[PDB]
Amino acid sequence: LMQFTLPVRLCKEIELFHFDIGPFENMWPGIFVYMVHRSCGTSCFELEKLCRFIMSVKKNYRRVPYHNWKHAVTVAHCMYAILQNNHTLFTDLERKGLLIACLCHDLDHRGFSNSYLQKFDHPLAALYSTSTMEQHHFSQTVSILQLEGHNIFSTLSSSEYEQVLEIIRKAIIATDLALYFGNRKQLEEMYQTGSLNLNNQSHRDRVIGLMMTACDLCSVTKLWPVTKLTANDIYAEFWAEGDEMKKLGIQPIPMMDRDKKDEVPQGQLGFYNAVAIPCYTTLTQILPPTEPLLKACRDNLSQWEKVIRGEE
Ligand SMILES: O=c1ccn(Cc2ccccc2)nc1-c1ccnn1-c1ccccc1
Ligand SMILES: [Mg+2]
Ligand SMILES: [Zn+2]
Image (cartoon, protein in one colour):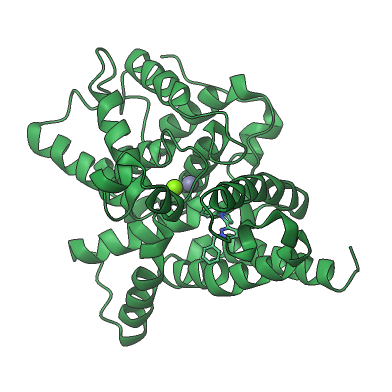
């Protein structure tokens, strides 16, 4: 059978949480199939259907600075690392579902927040009043799955198919960071009181949600040079949104104001402290082998503190 193989450095480094997929766009599909074959099996998907699905998903990501095809594959790799470090915790359908959910989680992103869509009065804001872009991303995923020769789940039973699309829907919705705060609090309480039960489906859902947030935020868990350079792409989109807010006659939050570029280092600290560190802390409590994500995140926090202190 046709197993995908990577050069030695990638073969070894792809196993590590802090792996960067590199600047060679044309290797990213092969990298994803490699991860599916090792995470799921060579039999999970028909290679011809999977390759066709991947290339349709790629085509439906836009040429935006951050919310692009590279982000999709980067988020799928973090999930690969979590699944490979927690072999026995996840079902066959979950391993299939979650890598696909990650690849598809920002399909057709325009580089704008749900907030900006609401203030613009975008049609999608009327179709989906909450988790606006996330319901769109799930919609695009179902659209692509329904293209001729793109149904990678065709060999699942009716019930297994409904289950995997339900895993994907919940996983993609959970990437709405507005939903992350409450989800982590609940997981924090369930862990502390000892009521967390991975046989409770509503509990698994919450844990998959936190994994999605962790994979989505995984830029902050890279080596400093990757984290620092990704921050430029993230802020390029924030500043364009801020520009579009000013065009609507609305002063944007400082994070999106390119006039307030001086405030970015302190804004990063807040994000690490309010979002990233709590996310990887709770994830590490629930799934101990994901500790390297927390360790790498703490290292990047310390780098941003150094930027503030003029040490860079
Ligand atoms: O660096 C960042 C700064 C701010 N925010 C958003 C935010 C800040 C404060 C309170 C709430 C929300 N996110 C990031 C970040 C790091 C990695 N990914 N993302 C990200 C996530 C979703 C969308 C776009 C980017
Ligand atoms: Mg998103
Ligand atoms: Zn994302």
